[PDB]
Length: 24
Image (tube, rainbow, N blue to C red; front, top):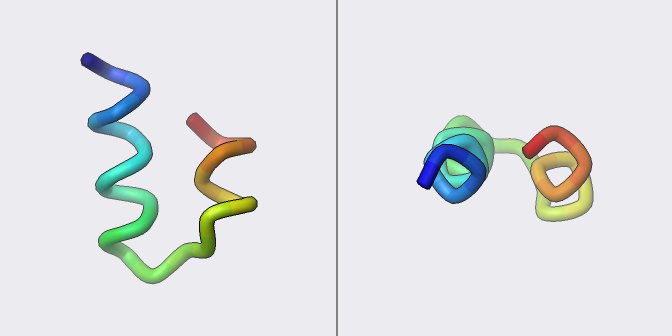
């Protein structure tokens, strides 16, 4: 769902895992 969706876009755009785990 939306957390996962968030996370894939966040990673896809170039952000690291620690950033995208915090964002999403």
